Length: 101
Length: 89
Image (cartoon, rainbow over all chains, first blue to last red; front, side):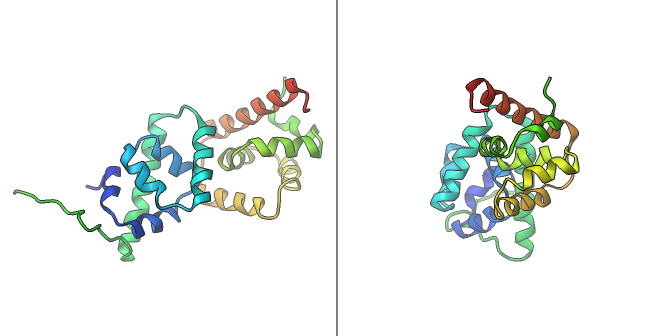
């Protein structure tokens, strides 16, 4: 039941490993549908240059379709799912939730 | 009217001025709707690495939709028109 905002509960190392399997177009389309907070969490884990290429693309693109944004997000979630099986995804320090049955 | 195959008639310098303005994704989708001689013309105008960066995209992408390929070719034609009314072409 993982959704795109759950990326906020993964450690910096996981996000960096996930950023290597996505291309520039998919990472940018997904960001147009992210919280200001997930955005900074994402920019913080990219090199100085990789981030500048990203801002280039974001300015270059313009108006995009909602469904294209949702598709880019699912493609990024499937990568995470794949890297999890190879044991490379780790939940952050305070990234756990208290539940009630 | 200017269609995508008419790019086979711009010279090397003009093509280098166009490749500068287009992003990786638009070029990959666009070339997926090109003849073999238009692909060769564009490839001899981009660096050994740029063509490597393009192979990656092309392979990372997989199957694509005809509407997106058409949308990518139109973006490039729009860039070409901007460059023409300027005088840079």
